[PDB]
Image (tube, rainbow, N blue to C red; front, side):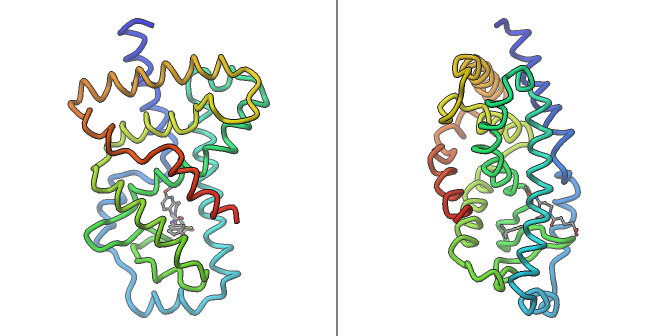
Length: 217
Ligand SMILES: COc1ccc2c(n1)CCN(C(=O)CCCC(=O)O)[C@H]2C(=O)Nc1cc(F)c2c(c1)CCC2(C)C
Protein backbone atom coordinates (compact mmCIF):
# COMPACT_ATOMS: atom_id res chain seq x y z
CA UNK A 1 0.00 0.00 0.00
CA UNK A 2 1.64 3.25 -1.25
CA UNK A 3 1.44 6.80 0.20
CA UNK A 4 -0.97 7.66 -2.67
CA UNK A 5 -3.28 4.74 -1.80
CA UNK A 6 -3.15 5.55 1.91
CA UNK A 7 -4.09 9.23 1.40
CA UNK A 8 -6.80 8.16 -1.05
CA UNK A 9 -8.16 5.92 1.72
CA UNK A 10 -8.08 8.74 4.31
CA UNK A 11 -9.95 11.09 1.94
CA UNK A 12 -12.41 8.39 1.05
CA UNK A 13 -13.26 7.47 4.66
CA UNK A 14 -13.65 11.21 5.45
CA UNK A 15 -15.93 11.69 2.45
CA UNK A 16 -18.16 8.73 3.50
CA UNK A 17 -18.34 10.17 6.99
CA UNK A 18 -19.32 13.61 5.63
CA UNK A 19 -22.07 12.09 3.51
CA UNK A 20 -23.48 9.97 6.37
CA UNK A 21 -23.00 12.17 9.49
CA UNK A 22 -26.77 13.09 9.72
CA UNK A 23 -26.23 16.23 11.77
CA UNK A 24 -23.76 18.76 10.29
CA UNK A 25 -21.19 20.01 12.84
CA UNK A 26 -21.94 23.57 11.71
CA UNK A 27 -25.63 23.24 12.65
CA UNK A 28 -24.86 21.60 16.04
CA UNK A 29 -22.47 24.36 17.17
CA UNK A 30 -24.86 27.17 16.10
CA UNK A 31 -27.75 25.48 17.96
CA UNK A 32 -25.71 25.22 21.24
CA UNK A 33 -27.27 28.52 22.38
CA UNK A 34 -30.79 27.07 21.73
CA UNK A 35 -31.49 25.40 25.08
CA UNK A 36 -34.70 23.81 26.40
CA UNK A 37 -36.50 26.09 28.87
CA UNK A 38 -37.39 24.87 32.37
CA UNK A 39 -41.01 24.56 31.19
CA UNK A 40 -39.93 22.37 28.28
CA UNK A 41 -37.68 20.19 30.47
CA UNK A 42 -40.60 19.65 32.84
CA UNK A 43 -42.76 18.67 29.81
CA UNK A 44 -40.29 15.97 28.89
CA UNK A 45 -40.09 14.78 32.51
CA UNK A 46 -43.88 14.40 32.69
CA UNK A 47 -44.03 12.13 29.63
CA UNK A 48 -44.34 8.37 30.11
CA UNK A 49 -41.25 6.18 29.99
CA UNK A 50 -43.03 4.48 27.08
CA UNK A 51 -43.20 7.72 25.14
CA UNK A 52 -39.63 8.72 25.92
CA UNK A 53 -38.47 5.22 24.91
CA UNK A 54 -40.43 5.51 21.60
CA UNK A 55 -38.86 8.89 20.86
CA UNK A 56 -35.32 7.86 21.85
CA UNK A 57 -35.51 4.47 20.15
CA UNK A 58 -36.71 6.15 16.95
CA UNK A 59 -33.92 8.76 16.90
CA UNK A 60 -31.19 6.26 17.77
CA UNK A 61 -32.51 3.71 15.24
CA UNK A 62 -32.31 6.36 12.58
CA UNK A 63 -28.73 7.17 13.76
CA UNK A 64 -27.89 3.47 13.45
CA UNK A 65 -29.12 3.57 9.80
CA UNK A 66 -26.66 6.40 9.02
CA UNK A 67 -23.90 4.27 10.54
CA UNK A 68 -24.88 1.32 8.32
CA UNK A 69 -24.68 3.67 5.30
CA UNK A 70 -21.24 4.83 6.46
CA UNK A 71 -20.10 1.18 6.60
CA UNK A 72 -21.47 0.50 3.13
CA UNK A 73 -19.34 3.34 1.70
CA UNK A 74 -16.07 2.08 3.27
CA UNK A 75 -13.59 0.59 0.81
CA UNK A 76 -13.87 -3.17 1.03
CA UNK A 77 -16.81 -3.44 3.39
CA UNK A 78 -19.32 -4.43 0.67
CA UNK A 79 -16.69 -6.88 -0.71
CA UNK A 80 -16.82 -8.88 2.62
CA UNK A 81 -19.20 -11.82 2.85
CA UNK A 82 -22.81 -11.46 4.04
CA UNK A 83 -22.11 -12.98 7.47
CA UNK A 84 -19.14 -10.72 8.29
CA UNK A 85 -20.91 -7.48 7.30
CA UNK A 86 -23.70 -8.25 9.76
CA UNK A 87 -21.41 -9.49 12.56
CA UNK A 88 -19.40 -6.24 12.35
CA UNK A 89 -22.46 -3.95 12.29
CA UNK A 90 -24.17 -5.86 15.10
CA UNK A 91 -21.08 -5.52 17.31
CA UNK A 92 -19.92 -1.98 16.34
CA UNK A 93 -22.80 0.23 15.11
CA UNK A 94 -24.03 1.25 18.53
CA UNK A 95 -20.45 2.00 19.61
CA UNK A 96 -20.13 4.31 16.58
CA UNK A 97 -23.39 6.13 17.49
CA UNK A 98 -22.02 6.64 20.98
CA UNK A 99 -18.78 8.18 19.56
CA UNK A 100 -20.72 10.34 17.05
CA UNK A 101 -22.73 11.64 19.97
CA UNK A 102 -19.81 13.66 21.36
CA UNK A 103 -20.29 16.12 18.48
CA UNK A 104 -23.78 16.90 19.71
CA UNK A 105 -22.57 17.39 23.31
CA UNK A 106 -21.70 20.77 24.89
CA UNK A 107 -19.22 20.46 27.81
CA UNK A 108 -19.60 24.07 29.01
CA UNK A 109 -23.18 23.45 30.20
CA UNK A 110 -23.29 19.58 30.05
CA UNK A 111 -26.09 19.43 27.47
CA UNK A 112 -26.81 17.29 24.41
CA UNK A 113 -28.82 17.89 21.22
CA UNK A 114 -32.30 16.29 21.25
CA UNK A 115 -35.37 17.11 19.20
CA UNK A 116 -34.20 20.55 18.01
CA UNK A 117 -32.55 21.96 21.18
CA UNK A 118 -29.92 21.27 23.86
CA UNK A 119 -30.93 19.78 27.20
CA UNK A 120 -29.14 18.24 30.19
CA UNK A 121 -29.51 14.68 31.46
CA UNK A 122 -32.54 15.55 33.62
CA UNK A 123 -34.49 15.79 30.34
CA UNK A 124 -34.46 11.94 30.28
CA UNK A 125 -35.70 11.47 33.85
CA UNK A 126 -38.85 9.47 32.79
CA UNK A 127 -36.63 6.66 31.39
CA UNK A 128 -35.66 5.81 34.96
CA UNK A 129 -32.01 4.96 34.26
CA UNK A 130 -29.94 7.86 35.53
CA UNK A 131 -26.82 5.60 35.72
CA UNK A 132 -26.78 4.62 32.04
CA UNK A 133 -27.58 8.20 31.04
CA UNK A 134 -24.88 9.77 33.28
CA UNK A 135 -22.31 7.32 31.96
CA UNK A 136 -23.21 8.28 28.37
CA UNK A 137 -22.86 11.92 29.40
CA UNK A 138 -19.50 11.24 31.14
CA UNK A 139 -18.23 9.40 28.07
CA UNK A 140 -19.27 12.23 25.72
CA UNK A 141 -17.76 14.63 28.23
CA UNK A 142 -14.36 12.91 28.29
CA UNK A 143 -14.38 12.69 24.46
CA UNK A 144 -15.31 16.37 24.17
CA UNK A 145 -12.10 17.40 26.01
CA UNK A 146 -10.08 15.96 23.08
CA UNK A 147 -11.72 18.33 20.54
CA UNK A 148 -12.17 15.45 18.11
CA UNK A 149 -12.09 16.77 14.55
CA UNK A 150 -14.61 15.50 11.97
CA UNK A 151 -11.91 13.54 10.17
CA UNK A 152 -10.50 11.96 13.40
CA UNK A 153 -14.08 10.81 14.15
CA UNK A 154 -14.44 9.38 10.62
CA UNK A 155 -11.21 7.40 10.83
CA UNK A 156 -11.69 6.33 14.43
CA UNK A 157 -15.27 5.13 13.88
CA UNK A 158 -14.18 3.24 10.78
CA UNK A 159 -11.85 1.36 13.14
CA UNK A 160 -14.59 0.77 15.70
CA UNK A 161 -16.44 -1.14 12.95
CA UNK A 162 -13.64 -2.90 11.08
CA UNK A 163 -12.45 -5.06 13.97
CA UNK A 164 -11.07 -8.52 13.07
CA UNK A 165 -11.45 -9.72 16.71
CA UNK A 166 -15.31 -9.71 16.60
CA UNK A 167 -16.48 -13.30 17.35
CA UNK A 168 -18.38 -15.08 14.55
CA UNK A 169 -16.27 -13.84 11.59
CA UNK A 170 -15.59 -16.26 8.69
CA UNK A 171 -13.12 -14.32 6.50
CA UNK A 172 -11.06 -13.10 9.51
CA UNK A 173 -8.02 -12.45 7.34
CA UNK A 174 -9.86 -10.18 4.86
CA UNK A 175 -11.17 -8.13 7.77
CA UNK A 176 -7.56 -7.93 9.15
CA UNK A 177 -6.32 -6.54 5.82
CA UNK A 178 -9.04 -3.91 5.90
CA UNK A 179 -8.35 -3.04 9.55
CA UNK A 180 -4.63 -2.82 8.85
CA UNK A 181 -5.13 -0.33 6.04
CA UNK A 182 -7.54 1.79 8.06
CA UNK A 183 -5.01 1.89 10.93
CA UNK A 184 -2.30 3.05 8.57
CA UNK A 185 -4.71 5.73 7.35
CA UNK A 186 -5.63 6.88 10.86
CA UNK A 187 -1.98 7.00 11.97
CA UNK A 188 -0.68 8.66 8.81
CA UNK A 189 -3.37 11.32 9.14
CA UNK A 190 -2.64 12.01 12.83
CA UNK A 191 1.01 12.45 11.77
CA UNK A 192 0.23 14.98 9.00
CA UNK A 193 -2.13 16.94 11.26
CA UNK A 194 0.20 16.82 14.38
CA UNK A 195 -2.56 15.07 16.37
CA UNK A 196 -0.59 11.96 17.52
CA UNK A 197 -1.29 13.02 21.12
CA UNK A 198 -4.91 11.90 21.02
CA UNK A 199 -3.93 8.22 20.58
CA UNK A 200 -3.05 7.77 24.26
CA UNK A 201 -6.37 9.49 25.29
CA UNK A 202 -8.88 7.55 23.21
CA UNK A 203 -11.07 5.28 25.36
CA UNK A 204 -9.97 1.57 25.48
CA UNK A 205 -11.83 -0.62 22.93
CA UNK A 206 -13.41 -2.81 25.69
CA UNK A 207 -14.67 0.42 27.40
CA UNK A 208 -16.96 1.11 24.39
CA UNK A 209 -18.28 -2.48 24.58
CA UNK A 210 -18.95 -2.24 28.42
CA UNK A 211 -21.48 0.68 27.99
CA UNK A 212 -23.28 -1.31 25.23
CA UNK A 213 -23.68 -4.32 27.59
CA UNK A 214 -26.00 -2.41 29.93
CA UNK A 215 -27.57 -0.64 26.88
CA UNK A 216 -28.85 -4.07 25.64
CA UNK A 217 -29.95 -4.99 29.24
C1 LIG B 1 -25.11 10.09 17.08
O1 LIG B 1 -25.26 11.43 17.57
C2 LIG B 1 -26.50 11.93 17.75
C3 LIG B 1 -26.69 12.83 18.81
C4 LIG B 1 -27.97 13.32 19.05
C5 LIG B 1 -29.00 12.94 18.18
C6 LIG B 1 -28.74 12.04 17.17
N1 LIG B 1 -27.52 11.57 16.97
C7 LIG B 1 -29.87 11.63 16.27
C8 LIG B 1 -30.65 12.93 15.97
N2 LIG B 1 -31.23 13.45 17.23
C9 LIG B 1 -32.47 13.95 17.35
O2 LIG B 1 -32.82 14.31 18.47
C10 LIG B 1 -33.32 14.08 16.10
C11 LIG B 1 -34.77 14.39 16.37
C12 LIG B 1 -35.41 15.02 15.15
C13 LIG B 1 -36.86 15.24 15.51
O3 LIG B 1 -37.22 16.21 16.16
O4 LIG B 1 -37.77 14.32 15.12
C14 LIG B 1 -30.41 13.28 18.36
C15 LIG B 1 -30.74 12.43 19.54
O5 LIG B 1 -31.34 11.40 19.29
N3 LIG B 1 -30.34 12.79 20.80
C16 LIG B 1 -30.41 11.93 21.89
C17 LIG B 1 -31.08 10.70 21.85
C18 LIG B 1 -31.02 9.81 22.92
F1 LIG B 1 -31.76 8.68 22.85
C19 LIG B 1 -30.21 10.09 24.03
C20 LIG B 1 -29.47 11.28 24.03
C21 LIG B 1 -29.55 12.18 22.97
C22 LIG B 1 -28.66 11.40 25.32
C23 LIG B 1 -29.26 10.32 26.27
C24 LIG B 1 -29.94 9.31 25.31
C25 LIG B 1 -29.05 8.10 25.06
C26 LIG B 1 -31.20 8.78 25.99
